[PDB]
Image (cartoon, coloured by chain):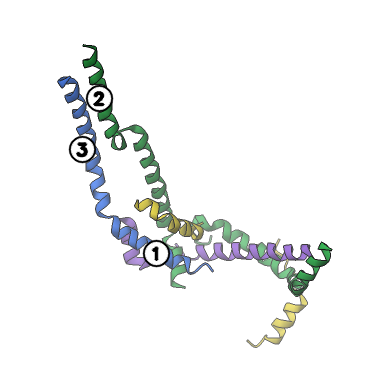
Amino acid sequence: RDLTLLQREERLRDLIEKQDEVLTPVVTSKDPFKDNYTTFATALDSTRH
Amino acid sequence: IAFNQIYANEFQMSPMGPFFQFVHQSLSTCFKELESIAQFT
Amino acid sequence: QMLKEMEKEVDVVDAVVRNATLNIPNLLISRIESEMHR
Amino acid sequence: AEINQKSLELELLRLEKETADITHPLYLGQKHQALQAMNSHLEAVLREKRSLRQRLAQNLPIEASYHRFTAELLPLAVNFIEKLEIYIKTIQTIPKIPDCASNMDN
């Protein structure tokens, strides 16, 4: 039982570590993008009517 | 990042592409609308 | 959550991003002649 | 012995359920798709930066995404001009449209 549970936890850790490495840069640049994009889209939308 | 950079520098090749599209779509809709009114009568 | 909140904006932006013998009608000729100076 | 085996199985299944949102291929696949759609969209926006700039500020060197609209605009304009009188008559009939609808109903 102990060996089997340890093997599964190790696999889970490996998977989480690989994801953290790639998600951290995207979350940090999110808020400036969303705000710049929304302002841009609203400005563009006012020229079509 | 590339967008934010262009948004800060340029938004915040000739720039003519969007004018053509708009005029084309608006004019087409106008055509069809008038034809429909005539047909109803 | 960010991707879902930006859907409407994407659409607007997408909308923007995406033998010629001419018989001129008398009505238009009359208009062009009356405003010819302008 | 039998109880011990089943108990282990239960423990394993519970661990898998609790971490599925971040680990299972199904859920991870959905997140990929959402991200690819946005990428493509941004690529397009960057490709048409000049035209978009000109609009905000308001062979022929025109961005390829707009060739169609540019080529078709001529015929469309010609057609409109030629049918101008018909469009004007039609517009004059617009106040009769409610009467026309009532007579037809009768």
User: In this rendering, is residue C5 above or below A2?
Assistant: below
Looking at the image, which is closer to me, B40 or D75? B40
The residue indicated by pointer 1 is: A40
Kindly identify the amino acid type of the residue bearing the numbered disc 1: Phe
Q: What chain is tagged by disc 2?
A: D
Mark 3, Cα crowd under 10 Å, few <14 / some 14-19 / many 20+, is few
Q: Quadrant of the C terminus of chain D?
A: bottom right
- Which shade of the palette goes to chain D? green
Kindly identify the amino acid type of the residue bearing the numbered disc 3: Glu
Q: What chain is tagged by disc 1?
A: A
- Which shade of the palette goes to chain B? purple
Mark toward the start of the polypeptide (3 vs 1) = 3
Looking at the image, which is closer to me, D6 or A3? D6
- Tell me if label 2 and label 1 are in contact, CB under 8 Å: no
Mark 2, Cα crowd under 10 Å, few <14 / some 14-19 / many 20+, is some
Return the x and y of residue A43 as percentages of the image width and height: 43, 68
Q: Residue at x 37, y 37 (%)?
A: D29
Whether residue D33 can be seen here: yes
The residue indicated by pointer 2 is: D12
Whether residue B15 can be seen here: no
The blue-tinted chain is A
Kindly identify the amino acid type of the residue bearing the numbered disc 2: Leu
Q: What chain is tagged by disc 3?
A: A
